[PDB]
Image (cartoon, rainbow, N blue to C red; front, side):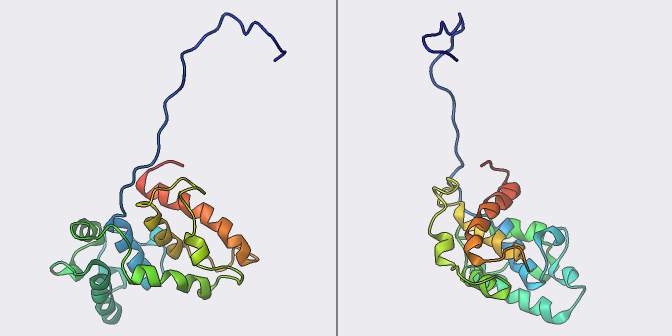
Length: 183
């Protein structure tokens, strides 16, 4: 529009509404999902919560016995008959005692992605160096994005690991679809 224009007879009130994501911690509904998915080399899109540890592996006795100890490290304990409790109900039991932040397995398995199929030139320290300004993510939300990064595990999606920092821009949205937040 031209300078010193009349701006028409139109008018409006000052300012407008705004919103931001809550600082709510991670839920066991995501941590349980990734710890089983990564053990079965499956994605969260192929792990139905409506099933059990014994039904997910097809009744295999070994993996069923390994997963029985994998949640005990990440939740400090496990409920009764967990190998007969589906993940859609087990997660509802795990959040009753979860610390709201990653366990020792779901924080150490994150660096294995960087050596499983990822290229070279990038690190896990520079992957968590910033998120509260790259996407505005609050401190309680950043702990769930790395869980979804471990379940994505691309076999080939980057020609250089210097571009893997731009790959974290996707993961922020992958997690938002799970909790229903906006970006």
